[PDB]
Image 1 (cartoon, chains in turn purple, brown):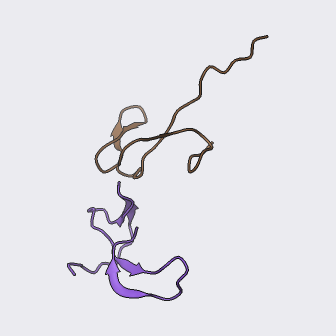
Image 2 (cartoon, each protein chain N blue to C red):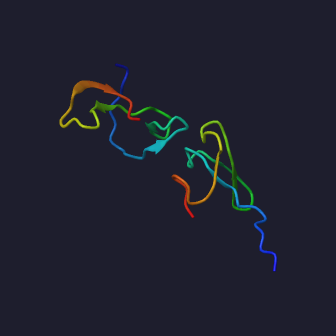
Length: 48
Length: 49
């Protein structure tokens, strides 16, 4: 719920293999299954 | 004529290479954001050759 909107895409990985920004702020994304097609669950969560 | 293997080179990969801290002489060390040093051989799994 506590998320902020941005535009630059300078992303990288941290030790936990989460795609974060320069400030170590975790990105959010949609959950789709390995066999799914379109978005399954619309609630965002960090990309692994 | 004794052909014997003397060892093999160790290869180290960290999950977050951007987070490695910079020492002198083109050298780095592991830090808390760089992850833990993953010790592996070459040409195995995700490692290069």
